[PDB]
Length: 137
Length: 137
Ligand SMILES: CCNC(=O)CSc1nnc(C(C)C)o1
Ligand SMILES: [Mn+2]
Ligand SMILES: [Mn+2]
Image (cartoon, rainbow over all chains, first blue to last red; front, side):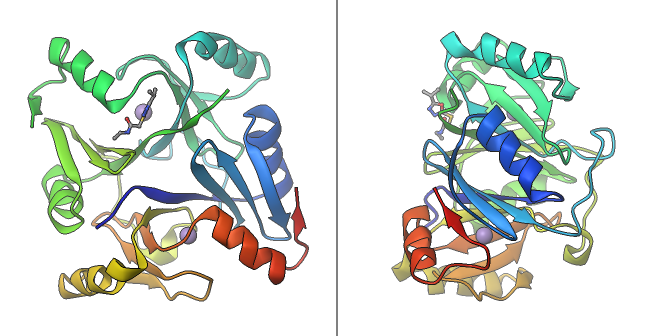
């Protein structure tokens, strides 16, 4: 039986700028780094950054919709998003199709998101404003 | 302040086989489905499958090391790996690290892993046998 996400591993092209992005800019906790990677946590999430010569800096129009959303409180959401904007962090999406979200890119173009709300809250919102053809189980 | 992973969204080329893989083969709970996606849970993980015509069925040699690991107990690991093997699910890597790991591909080539063990367990092993250049914080 699978019980959740054990870890998220992101391939990165340049380790130090990626560590700085996740630790300094996003505020995650850095636990260890080595010549080819780093381990961070964000709450319960174990994030691994893995130096990969295959990773390319990818513009958002070249990648699919696969993305990683991080939880933030309603009280903190807007000022965190505005700080990322003021820091020049690139974006990839503007239309809020899944609630209160801010869509931004990491240095390699990994698609990230700040989101306010749980799955239960999103299901409740969708009952009122459902996506086309939506069925609830 | 970011408090954890809010959700993981995977772009999928065909919704029905992806729902079958995550719900039926991998045992995740299907909460909702609409014409262009689905919401599932796996423990605390909120997973979204998003139908995306830009998703390519991608051979593992053509994607980088970015991957998504799910937690499973040691006791359940071998029978779950055998289930994936019976279903013909391809493996993209052999395990050479601490903690059991099974590295397998989803229908679109998303790189997945079953892993036994926490960040704390990994850090303890690393303290005893540090990787090249390893620093702790
Ligand atoms: C399947 C259950 N997992 C999730 O809903 C992850 S997002 C999530 N979980 N708690 C929260 C807070 C905003 C209350 O947000
Ligand atoms: Mn999202
Ligand atoms: Mn892994």
